Image (cartoon, coloured by chain):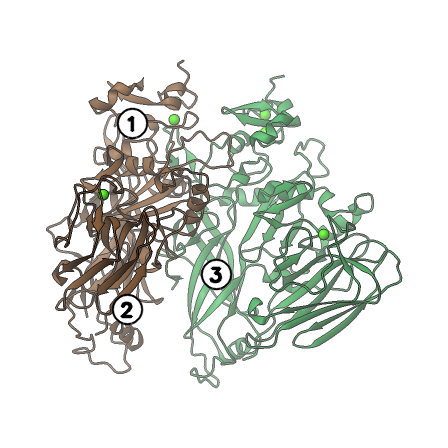
Chain colours: A brown, B green
Amino acid sequence: EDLDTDNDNIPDAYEKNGYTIKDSIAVKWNDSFAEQGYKKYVSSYLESNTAGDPYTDYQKASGSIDKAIKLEARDPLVAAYPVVGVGMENLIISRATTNSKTDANTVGVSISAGYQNGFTGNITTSYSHTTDNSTAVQDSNGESWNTGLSINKAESAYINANVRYYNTGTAPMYKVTPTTNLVLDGETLATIKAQDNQIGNNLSPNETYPKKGLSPLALNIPINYDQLKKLDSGKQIKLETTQVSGNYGTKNSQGQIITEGNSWSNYISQIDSVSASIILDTGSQTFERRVAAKEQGNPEDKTPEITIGEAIKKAFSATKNGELLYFNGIPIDESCVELIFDDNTSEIIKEQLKYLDDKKIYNVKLERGMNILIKVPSYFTNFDEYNNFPASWSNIDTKNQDGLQSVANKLSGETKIIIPMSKLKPYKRYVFSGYSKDPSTSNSITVNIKSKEQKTDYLVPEKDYTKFSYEFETTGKDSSDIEITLTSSGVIFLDNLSITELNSTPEIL
Amino acid sequence: EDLDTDNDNIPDAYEKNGYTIKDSIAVKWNDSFAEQGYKKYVSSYLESNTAGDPYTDYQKASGSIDKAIKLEARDPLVAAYPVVGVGMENLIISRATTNSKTDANTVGVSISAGYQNGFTGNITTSYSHTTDNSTAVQDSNGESWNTGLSINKAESAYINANVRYYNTGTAPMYKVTPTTNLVLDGETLATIKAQDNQIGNNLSPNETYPKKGLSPLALNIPINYDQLKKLDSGKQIKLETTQVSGNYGTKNSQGQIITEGNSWSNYISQIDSVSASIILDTGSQTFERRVAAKEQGNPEDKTPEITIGEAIKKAFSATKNGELLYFNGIPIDESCVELIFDDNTSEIIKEQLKYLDDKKIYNVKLERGMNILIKVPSYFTNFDEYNNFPASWSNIDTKNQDGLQSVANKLSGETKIIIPMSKLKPYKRYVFSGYSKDPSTSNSITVNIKSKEQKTDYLVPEKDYTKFSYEFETTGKDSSDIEITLTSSGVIFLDNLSITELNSTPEIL
Ligand SMILES: [Ca+2]
Ligand SMILES: [Ca+2]
Ligand SMILES: [Ca+2]
Ligand SMILES: [Ca+2]
Ligand SMILES: [Ca+2]
Ligand SMILES: [Ca+2]
């Protein structure tokens, strides 16, 4: 029982059934290690680099790699992979702006009344990655760009951009040389590549170049009246990185760290073709991960098969407290977040859910080629231990034990919540979602939402818990508050209420 | 029985009679492996690189190569070979366009009434590859380029192109540097080569640079009145890549992946001279493959000999369901697609068909220097399990068992089909093809096709099944529908009806 088919210092049996690294040697997994902090690693016994990255299974598991690599990349099934993009902070034509890395994913999402057959996720038509950045101009107050830039039919150029690089991956990049396009709708103004002074020497995960506390970088554009007025009328300019060139660190025979000749492009296509892509957006910081998966046809592919929940826990270092995952305290269970899939992933999940008795997305096996996006709600209450809503709900009755997880709220009457506009970002699309149950299957619920327009909807709860979602929008920072009223004709059980922010509606100057 | 003449870790006997890779070692083929997913590999025992590519037979069969290489390139008889071309998406002189990679092959194809001696294919005079790209300008509506570009005898230049690279091969290319010519009829405007910013760092098969969801690349042209009016009058500009330079990945002694010094041009001429070329066009995506073949003179050439159907199955990973091949569900049997050959391949197939009792193209041996193109029909019905026609046929009688494969349609009267123009691309040439049989050899069929011009033809079915083809054209998106009527004087058996799109007719502004 010491065979090593792939020659990476881990025996086949340990690599097949579970192992952990102690004193820099692989040992067989024992269930008593879990309380001591030891993690259970499983990988392929026919391949030395299971995930497709520059580091083998033993190097990743034992930590004999760059110490700037995230700890969740020490799992052989999670790839060490940089995700580097560029985003602008100032637009000079003299007005600031913000950037969003998950707007393109969300724009092509349509929200309906309810969900069928236990599939509580959502489908997007324009799935994209965190490197596709869309900037929203702040502090406008209906001041068109033409005021002070008087133009009739001239292409006067005079636009300046202050960019900053970001890394949402698990590995650092060295000698970062990005290539970007600044496009408004479909017009490629230029293909600008960092020549010699906009090269970042190093860029750690969750960090920017230049680091926080430094002025944004400036890289060095003609613009005509047509696209200028397009920008003036409900359009946001976008900055997309087509490619980034950079290096990774490895040890010499002398023990030094080198990055020259260690191009990250030698591995990008291999990693992207042997794994599934997952994105987590907590509302302030975004993470993108690649998790290795099996190809269905090959009988000689020995990559371990794990579920979606196991993949999420391994990739984002979530903590399993009982049966639910927590990311730094934020609940990220399938009933506490918003799950967005492309068409193929949604079809696969729907097909697999027919034969699954649990009817949970997190119990569906993970397959390569998938694309998953998790949106953590801006506000979420479950009536059990977590409530981050700015204003407490009215008529709250927690004296129940029939909740989705622990307890529920007994709706006998009406529940109204008020939200000041200062707690929400202006010109955004939001979704209010929840789970409802009517054991008698006789009662009905009316939902009234006060927004830029008044909305009223009617839903009939079923015997068991079902999910409902309703969308609304916000207009202007200096406007009225948001009122949400849920009224029931009888007794209803409510649980897992949340409000999450979707993409931003157009700004009309 | 352990000889290894070529020293590639596969014994001569296994390599001669059939082998498969299990636990990273070669084992003798057994017929009981087929249901377990194992493929049967055969190669040459006198050469380590049977197909001529950078990877040996053992590396390809065992998968010890780049994980971005397609699985069908793991067969030693199918080469790992990039096919990189360039195609434009926007033409600015302010109007969009589309690209076609198989128009040049199809333009030189003449369609006749019937086929003789069991040869159901077609002959082309201008066979070309997927790197020869012809663009068709969309959304014209008879608006000449001179309107707004008023020119009498001046060469005012002012043309802009937005290009995008594509890969139809089985292997990725690294550091892509294409060289292209933008030519209208025979005028070489310039020989433009990607200098420093239009270099794609990596380009996987079935993918583009920049990837889908990114703005098209712009590379940086004088044009005179003569060729401008030529373009105005029924001419489409073409963009041909003369050569592309790029690299492939290989493993170090340290186990890293390197692409520097690994030029793809060291192998192009060798692969092209030791193989046959096959192209498959499903109507939306196109694939080009090279399959190794034997040279006739050499008695010391040990390359295995396979038929055309075996070559197609190996090259495109088709599935043999019974006796017919399916490509992702699309039937690609010789009676369900359009086969186009150049002159030499057609002559060889005709010569070999004389001694073949089966009289099938797919049973003819494959030889090097061949050139095969497969066009999947836009619409196809076989009355057995597959029918993707937009509108169901009239007077359908499937109560028969005398079909070409399973059942046929009994024509006693007339069959009429209507096709809305929204289901067809305007300004295109189409072919309606089918198989007919008259056991009594007494009846006759009249075919009436309503198109830009009204066409009527008469055919006399033979005792057994024979193929008929009739061509027509479409004009304008906003026009009348297409009517096809087949009328029989008696009882006829019809099977395998299809409509396939040929090249595009000239556009007159
Ligand atoms: Ca091992
Ligand atoms: Ca391994
Ligand atoms: Ca609860
Ligand atoms: Ca051998
Ligand atoms: Ca060999
Ligand atoms: Ca049939």
The mark closer to the camera, 3 or 2, is 2
Q: Position of residue A349 (x, y in %)?
A: 42, 44
**Pointer 2: residues within 10 angstroms few (<14), some, or many (20+)?**
some
Quadrant of the frame with the C terminus of chain B? bottom right
Q: Which residue is mark 3?
A: B87
Q: Secondary structure at mark 1?
A: helix
Quadrant of the frame with the N terminus of chain B? top right
Does the image show residue A204?
Answer: no
Q: Which residue is mark 2?
A: A235
Q: Position of residue A501 (x, y in %)?
A: 24, 56
Residue type, numbered disc 3: Gly
Q: Chain of mark 3?
A: B
Label number found at residue B228: none
Above/below status of A320 relative to A371: above
Q: What distance separates the C-alpha of mark 1 from that of mark 2? A: 47 Å
Please state which of residues B337 and B486 is positioned toward the viewer in this rendering. B486
Above/below status of B367 relative to B445: above
Q: Are marks 3 and 2 in contact (CB under 8 Å)?
A: no
Q: Is residue B402 left or right of residue A12?
A: right
**Pointer 3: residues within 10 angstroms few (<14), some, or many (20+)?**
many
Residue type, numbered disc 1: Ala
Q: Position of residue A37 (x, y in %)?
A: 21, 25
